Amino acid sequence: PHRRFEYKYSFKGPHLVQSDGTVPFWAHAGNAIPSSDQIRVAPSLKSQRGSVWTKTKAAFENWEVEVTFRVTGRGRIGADGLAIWYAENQGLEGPVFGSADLWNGVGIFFDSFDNDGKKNNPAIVIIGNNGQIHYDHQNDGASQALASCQRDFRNKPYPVRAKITYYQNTLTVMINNGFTPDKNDYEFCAKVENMIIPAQGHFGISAATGGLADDHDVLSFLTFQLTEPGKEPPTPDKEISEKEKEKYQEEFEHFQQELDKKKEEFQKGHPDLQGQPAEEIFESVGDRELRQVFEGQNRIHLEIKQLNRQLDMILDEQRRYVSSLT
Amino acid sequence: PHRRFEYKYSFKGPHLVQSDGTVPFWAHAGNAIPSSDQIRVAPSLKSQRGSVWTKTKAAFENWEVEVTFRVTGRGRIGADGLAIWYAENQGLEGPVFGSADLWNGVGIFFDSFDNDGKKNNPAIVIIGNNGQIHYDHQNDGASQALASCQRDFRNKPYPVRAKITYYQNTLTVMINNGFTPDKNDYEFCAKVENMIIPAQGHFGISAATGGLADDHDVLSFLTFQLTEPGKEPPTPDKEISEKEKEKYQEEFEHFQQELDKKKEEFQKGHPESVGDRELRQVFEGQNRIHLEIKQLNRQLDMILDEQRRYVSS
Amino acid sequence: PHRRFEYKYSFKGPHLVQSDGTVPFWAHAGNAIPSSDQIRVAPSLKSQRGSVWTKTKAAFENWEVEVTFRVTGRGRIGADGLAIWYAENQGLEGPVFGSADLWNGVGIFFDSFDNDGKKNNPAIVIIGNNGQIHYDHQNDGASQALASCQRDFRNKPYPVRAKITYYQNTLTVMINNGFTPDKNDYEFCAKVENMIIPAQGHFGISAATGGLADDHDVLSFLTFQLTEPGKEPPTPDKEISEKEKEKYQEEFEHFQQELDKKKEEFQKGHPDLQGQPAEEIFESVGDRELRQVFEGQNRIHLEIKQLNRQLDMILDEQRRYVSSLT
Amino acid sequence: PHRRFEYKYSFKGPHLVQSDGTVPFWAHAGNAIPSSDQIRVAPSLKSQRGSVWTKTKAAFENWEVEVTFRVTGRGRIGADGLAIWYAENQGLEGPVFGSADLWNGVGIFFDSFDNDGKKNNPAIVIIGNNGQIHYDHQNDGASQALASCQRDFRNKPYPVRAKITYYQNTLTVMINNGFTPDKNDYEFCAKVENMIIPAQGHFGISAATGGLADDHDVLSFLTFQLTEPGKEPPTPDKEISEKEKEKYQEEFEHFQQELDKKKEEFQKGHPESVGDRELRQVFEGQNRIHLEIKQLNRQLDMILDEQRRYVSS
Amino acid sequence: GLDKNTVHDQEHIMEHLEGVINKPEAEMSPQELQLHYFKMHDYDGNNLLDGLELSTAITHVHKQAPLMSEDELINIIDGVLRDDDKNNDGYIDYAEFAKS
Amino acid sequence: GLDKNTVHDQEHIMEHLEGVINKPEAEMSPQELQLHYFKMHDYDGNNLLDGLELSTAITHVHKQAPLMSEDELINIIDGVLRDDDKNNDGYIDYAEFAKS
Amino acid sequence: GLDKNTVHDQEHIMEHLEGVINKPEAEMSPQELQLHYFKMHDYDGNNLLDGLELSTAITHVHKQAPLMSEDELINIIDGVLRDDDKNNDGYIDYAEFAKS
Amino acid sequence: GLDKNTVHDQEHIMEHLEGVINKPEAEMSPQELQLHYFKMHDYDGNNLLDGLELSTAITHVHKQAPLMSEDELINIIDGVLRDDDKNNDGYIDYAEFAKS
Ligand SMILES: [Ca+2]
Ligand SMILES: [Ca+2]
Ligand SMILES: [Ca+2]
Ligand SMILES: [Ca+2]
Ligand SMILES: [Ca+2]
Ligand SMILES: [Ca+2]
Ligand SMILES: [Ca+2]
Ligand SMILES: [Ca+2]
Ligand SMILES: [Ca+2]
Ligand SMILES: [Ca+2]
Ligand SMILES: [Ca+2]
Ligand SMILES: [Ca+2]
Ligand SMILES: [Ca+2]
Ligand SMILES: [Ca+2]
Ligand SMILES: [Ca+2]
Ligand SMILES: [Ca+2]
Ligand SMILES: [Zn+2]
Ligand SMILES: [Zn+2]
Ligand SMILES: [Zn+2]
Ligand SMILES: [Zn+2]
């Protein structure tokens, strides 16, 4: 289908927040911390709840939503987790992943904690609700689940990219798990066929944290209206001539390569310019634990060196005392 | 020395923040996030500054502060770092570890980023100031370092503990590196003799984050007034009778065990993991090896000095 | 639907093998080791390949297959893995999970190694082949996959139970991951709709092992013919009377409880009867590594005790020598 | 003692089994599974017995065997166990660790299951036999144990190594527990003095599994004939000229480095993980601590005995 | 082939009950020992005798005669299932067993 | 402000006891309930009460009420410390607490 | 609202190119600096100007005046997109930018 | 059996060199190829050849041939050890190998 980007229902860096300190076209509430690069919906503190919702309602019969997010934790178990919503009303605060219950719409829940005890978490659960059903958070929504895929999204070297597509009453969620830096590496997670959602509603993200604490960050939210090939606009007749289209782009590319050649010799011209790698950023929990043990052994090593030196001194002085007396 | 705990210049859990949303007796500013269990002075976001400062000034000739904190980050490299201040005025915001420059007092800087490039970070730097010198951010304060240190306080299994003591015009910084959950496991890190500080100032804590981001959480900050054993005036008959204390304490120690016995059956009447316990056992074994080797060092010192007495004869 | 157990296409313990040393109605080949409790299709040795296939072909329009299996490994990464087949011809030996390629049928591959490098293994992949397509083992069959669910089946406290149902040209795979001892705890893994398989074929299991080595064991294979409620046999008119059915079962239950009461007081009558728990059997790889480190510290502890005792002796003897001279 | 390696009574990788499917010079029987890298003498299945025995008998007055093996099981409790035999005849099948009872010779039993219930397993038990006594399975051979030991050879990061030496009618069993990849890291486990064994017998290895199941894999089995330094007859001029040896060895040591330099660029011309390297570093650090403490013990012994010489004067 | 005297045999039932139950009975009613015969070969515990359990009931290892061939075993099991099982479940309940 | 009735409130000690102690209490001696008051307001586990703990004791919301100004709580805590703590450690022992 | 003098302004282009490129140019052709203007605000790197990048192009933080309200910003961005974007993609290519 | 031509086979040393060494060889000195023969048949890395390694050297299948009886290989290896090994260590040094 044909894709149209919608700016009023999207947000991204590196200028995510205005000078006021609020995301354009989005209202944030709870413990959300909007920054210039991402939104920390729930910080790694006990009992945090945050949400960011669109101000204006979106009337799209078919849509695509691309959410880039990172969920980080110190331990192996994680907090309550994240949730992407397309509802009728702004949930804001509440008990369901930092948002209100009894929502009329669709919710894709990235649940990191195993309340049910089934040992199948973290997971991605597609749940559609009509405003009368209550989400059973102690059961991880197992009875109410319309779709469930068990894909670990916590503690990844690269941000996790979820793509949620509503098209022909079919909702498909495809996830790039963040093992590779390539953005276009999406893999199928789940689908729901023949689901009815409200005709117009608000997009939203929410996050919550229980006894264990995770950092839930959303780097970018991207919204695309989808149009069928049969239902396309009649013509892009507005375009004047293809000749100017074949006259402008080579000048644009010539400018790009000239700018690159202008950049190259002066990147090395100023010695203060440097570069920092990102290899140190990623470390697994068990790897960090083993490194901590290796660091802990250094005290023992230094104390053994101290003991050896003291033994050397006592041996030498006993030697010289024995020589002196004899 | 005799220690008197001062509640006005201290904060700790498990109820650290009131229902209003502010730390009692402390003013937070910047990107600090006070919570029930700790204060996240600077979160792991780009360009974050935070500070928590006492409201009322402290008039102590000798003092001691014990600070428990965690500096946790995804990367091996660290953020700008953490700072503990005894100043004249509340710095609040500023460019020196999230607090104001040109302070009149002393600042203990836990610096986790190597701006100078000398490969000597993270480190603990004690810097005194009188208000007429700028802190050198790019040189990590090496030029004005009264004392220095080299300890890694980042990403430790247990929270890092620091005891900073001003006694007889001497400042001593002792650090438990966070490899053991023992509170009184401090090891000597730095000291400065004959340092003058303002006789009445504010106690503050601050944190800052640069391009790389760490979370600087402060779990507790306990301030003690120190007095000399001879300078403390003893008041006769001020204390209660000793026999009454004995009777009270014996009934209290009986009743606490009675309460424990009451709770033991009911906890299972109405209803740590593997690997975590294994890691805890590994760290306990490392601590046991460390303590045994220190005991061997003490025994070596004892036999050495007894041999010195014998050699003298 | 109505279920009928088929013994000729099934095998289970605790009498899995006859006195000859072969599974009844099944032919084994390769490095398979049929035992009295399970079949070790591929032992934990380098370059092992094993297969067990039914002798007679099964002509079922709808069927259910329940495979109980255990895949165990010392490390975190595993061998090539296991495969369940419903083919036209017996694959026996070959390069595809210990069985031949170019199979005409359906294969559910429990793949434990990540040949593609996508970091999405272990996984369960449903692949249908018609005899002309070649399984791309270096690509984990990603291009040829008809279904893929990422469920970790390696190193589980209880055996993993997969249920594969072909019904109305729909193939559903539901997996109990082995976290709980309850057999009837199946969770949905994958489905394929409108797939055409050969009308009659052989059931089979195969397993293979690459550079890394895993133990692949099959405890039980159970086959059920499925009949639609519309397509049921006309009547179970053969049954004579319900009165005898209501006369026999209470006598049977009375015998069962009498046998239990006969057993109870004589279980404790003989003191040699004991009981062994199964808690020791399960341990994770990282848990075993940490326990190995803890065991390794004991040498250091004992050597420190030896040093302390020697220091005590030297201190005491220097003390007595000093006292004697003075 | 001078050691001569005997290939006929040995087996090792990386080509352990021929294309026929049998170990050279060795006959396997029972549930043993010879492979290219090791022999799985008993797999982790219920009621498995396996044995590998030499074909030709050995006539050595003094001998030494080095066996590398792994006993790996899912559970903390172990199977029946492993056995190393110097016997008169090939036991093959039987009830004593998968080999025949009533053996005439010596058996070193690595027993990992506590049949007796004395909580002293796993253990290494040396049992001599003349053919007229049954091995007591239920008592773990405690009654007829010439020597004993207590080491855990199950589920170790590195393969467990054992050196069994018959010299001057004395049998010594030394064990590297598998905490280090060093081959010559043996520690004393047991010894028996003045034990008589048959002057010509077979070398065998065996394993058995009871209700609980372990995999007993033997990676290598190297047998050396031992001769005394004085008993060895020296042949004059049998060795080559020393200068010719020097020229040969210097050209060989040049050419091996030349080959390494040749391979280094081409390996990357046409093209261990994190955590595994961390675990290896942890084990290396533990070994370093162990070696340093042993060095401290040796220094303590040196100062102690020098003080004894001084006290004598 | 599931003969009446085979299930009604006392010695076979006594050998199977040896060890598991510590009360040896000199005599037993044919119905009682047929309940024991149904209970002993139900290894899974579902109180139903399927083809695989009858395979170990017919062929046996008792401590001889060569083990029965695959075709004859298939014929005997198929005959027993076709005669005694009327619910088409593939199993034999105790009512089905006691009926024939 | 360390009032006798506030320490002797049966319902308040019952509210603190709810959850942690499954067994409820109906009648209680004054020493019993004052020891519950001392133990429930001792979170650190050092068996001593300091100003930071008495601040929580006086100004915890329960289940409304205006939050006390810091000056008033400073005065109350200072009065308690001066009246009861003869130790001058900054910590209130149960001897010092039980005097009042 | 994407005025011709706004993109054609030399000082704005010079401030944005300050630091990133180390060659300051005293004069530049309007087409050259309009290519620079298109390149500077394409933060993502896809060579397309969407609404979110024009939001940071119109509203700004330069080191004043209060930040432009949400409704006016929405109207300006919607007008620019409706006038210059004809392919209904939601983005503006350099051909679309140079046309208007 | 440690024949001069078998050690001097250019194609056999090339076959052993394939894979491990990316660069192929066309002409080779006798010392060069005999050192390749010594190194490729030294798997343990001890720079010494023993009977277990010479057994693989003589009786490895490559790409047929009847597998040699154990007695013949015993005779060949014993002859090599007696002729070349003056060391009596049970190991063949490259001095001992280069004598023949
Ligand atoms: Ca959950
Ligand atoms: Ca769950
Ligand atoms: Ca710095
Ligand atoms: Ca520095
Ligand atoms: Ca694979
Ligand atoms: Ca894969
Ligand atoms: Ca035993
Ligand atoms: Ca024992
Ligand atoms: Ca049954
Ligand atoms: Ca039936
Ligand atoms: Ca307290
Ligand atoms: Ca006190
Ligand atoms: Ca763009
Ligand atoms: Ca466009
Ligand atoms: Ca060698
Ligand atoms: Ca030699
Ligand atoms: Zn029988
Ligand atoms: Zn209360
Ligand atoms: Zn600008
Ligand atoms: Zn070759």
Image (cartoon, coloured by chain):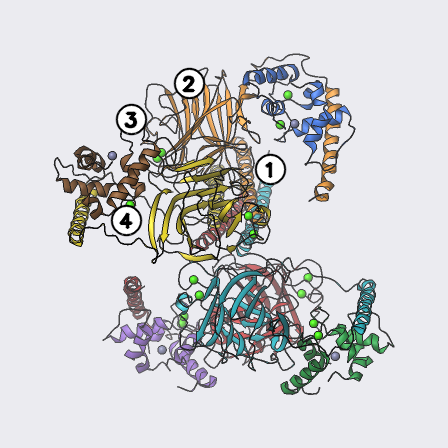
Chain colours: A yellow, B orange, C cyan, D red, E green, F blue, G brown, H purple
Residue linked to disc 2: B89
What chain does mark 3 sit on? G
Residue at 50%, 64% in the rendered image: C191
Please identify, in this view, whether the residue under mark 1 or under mark 4 is nearer the observer.
4
**Residue kind at label 3, given as amino acid type:** Ala
Q: Could you say where residue A136 lies in the image, as x and y percent from the top left?
A: 58, 47
Specify whether disc 4 shares its chain with disc 3: yes
Mark 3 against mark 1, which lies toward the viewer? 3
SS under mark 1: helix
Mark 2 residue element: loop
> Looking at the image, which residue is at 67% across and 83% down?
E78
Q: On the image, numbered disc 4 is attached to which residue?
A: G46
Q: Which mark is residue G65?
A: 3
Q: Are marks 2 and 1 in contact (CB under 8 Å)?
A: no
**What is the C-alpha distance between the residues marked 1 and 4?**
84 Å
> Which mark's residue is nearer the viewer, 4 or 3?
3
